[PDB]
Length: 155
Length: 155
Image (cartoon, rainbow over all chains, first blue to last red; front, side, top):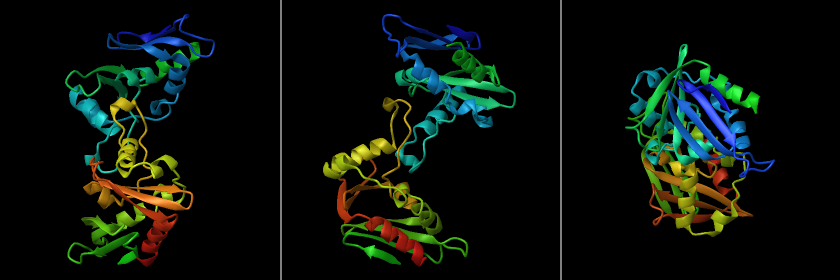
């Protein structure tokens, strides 16, 4: 199943019949972001989908003007800083506000963040601590949520 | 001011008149733990005291049988794991349940945890990621809270 538009944002997912049981739809899940695909063949789609439905961005704004306007490289480093603060930071509560990776994707090491500005939005993504190779794609605001919501409706 | 018993657990704190303003008591704070002292001369006592009053252990139990009975070295590593999970852990929410350092202390790098068992309790402490030189002192259960509560009463 494929919801959204791979040139901007889409989710592609399917169970593999031979990996699965009536309880566990096990198979593949990927995000297309500005034409690029990051994917995992390690997903249990019920668990991934129920967790996408409870991302902070589904019911709250994730406005951040700085992160929108700075480099993809710097933003991804700052977002990974917020999510995984070190002991230099003191005793700081971690921040997953902007994180929108499905669990299968996070668990492989794809960290994918949503930042909104006014009427636009950015997915900012990279692999692990490789901030140099980070990237992003400009979306319309609400586009990510609406694609997610579509995936949940169609299942 | 000094509340508790340095041979088990005490808090020692005072404003420094020259660092302070009528609005802010700025000065020193230390924890004595089994006769050992860890201290900071960079504490704002209002902020430290109000944050001690809201530690998870003031309202909730922090029973943990494993952490009580294992090595100080291993327990401190496991507690620092929970508090500062890495990207290996996936996208996991940090855990400060057991942390009881005042902020001035955690900001310098003293991480001090409370673990309860039955009728007893342990402060488990170390500096930064130095799990080898960790240590602990056995307290009576409720002793830590009671000293904290005493510091708040006397201010």
